[PDB]
Amino acid sequence: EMAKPVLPDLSGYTTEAALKKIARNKPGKITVARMMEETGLKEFIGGDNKMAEWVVRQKGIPQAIMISDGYVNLQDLVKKVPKQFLSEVSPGVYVARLPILVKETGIFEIDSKTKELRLSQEKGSFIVSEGKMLITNTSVNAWSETRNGLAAYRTPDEFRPFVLTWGGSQTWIAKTKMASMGYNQSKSYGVSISQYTPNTAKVLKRGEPTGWIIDSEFADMWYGFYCYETRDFVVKGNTYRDNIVYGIAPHDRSHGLIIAENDVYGTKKKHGIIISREVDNSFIFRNKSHNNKLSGVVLDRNSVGNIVAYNEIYQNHTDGITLYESGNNLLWGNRVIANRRHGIRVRNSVNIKLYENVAMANGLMGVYGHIKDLNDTDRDIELDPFDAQVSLIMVGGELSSNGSGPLSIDSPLSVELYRVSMLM
């Protein structure tokens, strides 16, 4: 019998507040130099021996547009960078034919002056930032010069331009549209916020990256959003639609995240929203997650101490919410409606608290709890251990009109139920 959760205040996460976030007074230095001189690029590309695909895209030794030692905007880049590498094809509309690296001391901005920054698929363009970067009231899209359109998704391994930020960086995106980014390659999922690989991290010690993404739209992305060892990142007021694998997908010891008031739908292969592998102490609230190929919302691989609250979770093709091996979480007052399978499913998770959830008209159970032996499976039990136990407490809310019944919990360690409505 606890009190309603205290959810983080979202009032200060606005475009106006984001504009006031970078230092524009000290102009920066613009260089077109070699990719493989830079840690920001080697870190995910690999050694000199991995440079060939880039040599092919660029038809020469691989280069990048590099920003450092101060502030640079897109309009600045256009003037100082050769037209072959960054062209204005119509007013406000640019095509980058090289990648852009914001170095550690760089500060990079795109604003409403830019109608569209097109990143060339053929030429191998992408955006990496180790510094400060702000993108507002504009469009950054993965662009196919061959098709003269968006680099629309076709196959997992086909390169598409992406955005990636490294440890010690800070990023703010607001009122921006991005489409067709990312593919099945490390750090290249689409929009990725990431700490350095552990080897590079024990050296640089740059500390975890952070930032906001607000009131923006992301479409046809491999992952709408991805992060790795990321702190207090904010994702609010966005639309993630028709993305490929995942809508919003925090990973790997990220924490303090705020994922709120997003509308996530139409995910083609998997989940609307997933936090996987020790994504702890985060907040998932007031989102709509619907019509996704698998679950509406997933907590995976020992992702603990989270609050999932007041989300509208409906018409997903499997579960509303699935908890996989992720104990000690609170689900408060979610409305989980008309998902094809279960409303809320809990596998191998203990101390799950279900308070005031409405689970209605799902195809199977309203709430389904079970255990499963994961030893003879593809699971790396060293990296991701598990315990075949399930336990939960349910208080209030309502379970009704579900296809297979209100609840089923098989072989529970313990289940307590208090004043849950289950209508006949």
Image (spheres, rainbow, N blue to C red):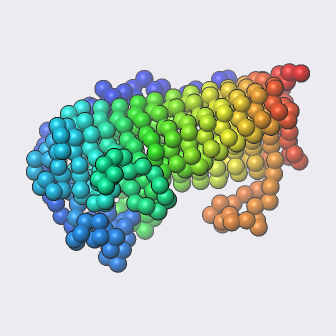
Residue 395 appears in which quarter of the rendering? top right
Residue 50 vs 278, above or below: the answer is below
Q: Is residue 117 left or right of residue 91?
A: right
Look at 22% across and 64% down and name the residue there.
63
Residue 382 appears in which quarter of the rendering? bottom right
Look at 55% across and 36% down and name the residue there.
265
Camera-side residue: 183 or 235? 183
Query: Is residue 275 in view from this perspective?
Result: no
Residue 41 appears in which quarter of the rendering? bottom left
- How many numbered markers are drawn? 0
Q: Is residue 218 left or right of residue 405?
A: left
The quarter in which the C terminus is drawn is top right
- Residue found at the very far left of the displayed protein: 80
Camera-side residue: 371 or 271? 271
Give x and y (percent) for residue 306.
61, 39
Residue 2 vs 243, above or below: the answer is above
Give x and y (percent) for residue 117.
26, 44
Q: Is residue 233 left or right of residue 245?
A: left
Camera-side residue: 119 or 377? 119
Residue 226 vs 217, above or below: the answer is below
Look at 22% across and 37% down and name the residue there.
114
Give x and y (percent) for residue 413.
85, 46
Q: Is residue 261 left or right of residue 412?
A: left
Query: Is residue 173 in view from this perspective?
Result: yes
The quarter in which the N terminus is drawn is top right
Look at 81% across and 26% down and name the residue there.
401
Give x and y (percent) for residue 396.
78, 23
- Residue found at the very far front of the displayed protein: 147
- Residue found at the very far bottom of the displayed protein: 49
